Length: 168
Image (spheres, rainbow, N blue to C red):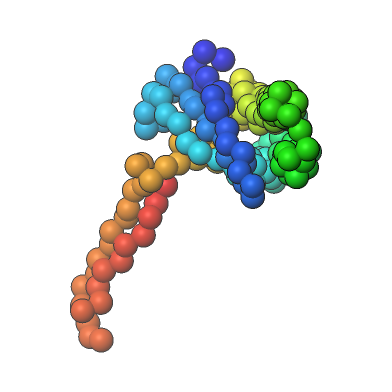
């Protein structure tokens, strides 16, 4: 519990995408840093869940259900219809309806952020699953901690003796 604390402090709704800031505070020796944040989308959560489900060792374990898919269709439909009718409304009527629209966006955000956040928090509190290496990668993988492995061989007789590849 206290050893690995995860939250989603903010999220972004775009026309074609929803992004979550995943923020971690940890004392665990395994992590590069004690505090860090990454950006993740729903499909990354689904990947993590699928990976844990397919892990043989975790048979007989209760895996936290995957988050629900983010759906901003409702608010975005109302946003369009409100735009169509802007000419037919007073300043005060329009602003009221913009308030209700923003209240609906807020309710959707609240529900989907909680769904994604709880999933990670349940993993963080599981004595076994909190150690999973894919879970670790989900939380901290970033351009800043990319590592590269360099290899070289002697030549004879085709220069072309070196290899580079990213490693986790």
